[PDB]
Image (spheres, grey):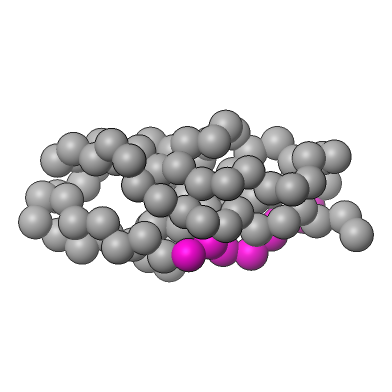
Amino acid sequence: HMAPTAPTNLASTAQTTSSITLSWTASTDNVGVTGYDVYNGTALATTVTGTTATISGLAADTSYTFTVKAKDAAGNVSAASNAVSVKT
């Protein structure tokens, strides 16, 4: 029992024609966790450390799948959250 839990119940609140804001439930564990990571498709995108996320550089009228991954300051990462299909 070292690595944290994978963020669950992801969602999307504010989303413009370039910048988007993601929200999700924090990990039940926080003994070594520092921040989260947002995946855009199959590669790492933006990075955060709170309960939200900001992704810039997004073309309009396009499909974008995002997710979240909790990390630890010791080399321990959790699983990926649900894929959020947002249309910019």
In the image, what residue occupies the spot 41% across and 51% down?
11
Query: Which residues are drawn in magenta?
Result: 75-82
Query: How would you classify the magenta stretch by its main secondary structure?
Result: loop
Q: Where does the image place residue 38, in percent across and percent down from the top left?
A: 47, 50
- Whether 80 is among the magenta residues is yes
Which residue in the rendered view is the most extreme toward the right?
Answer: 1
Please state which of residues 8 and 78 is positioned toward the viewer in this rendering: 8
Quadrant including the N terminus: bottom right
What residue do we see at 47% from left, 54% from top?
10
Residue 23 shows up from this direction: yes
* Position in image of residue 22 (x %, y %): 40, 43
Residue in the picture at 64% in, 50% down: 70
Horizontal relation, residue 21 to residue 71: left or right = left
The answer to which quarter of the image holds residue 8 is bottom right
* Residue 73 showing in the rendered view: no
Residue found farthest to the left? 61
Q: Which residue is rendered at x = 19% and y = 56% of the image? A: 87
Quick check: 83 left or right of 35?
left
Residue 5, x across and y down, in percent:
72, 56
Query: 73 or 32, which is in the foreground?
Result: 32
Q: Position of residue 7 (x, y in %)?
A: 60, 54
Q: Is residue 66 above or below residue 16?
A: below
What is the number of callouts on the image? 0
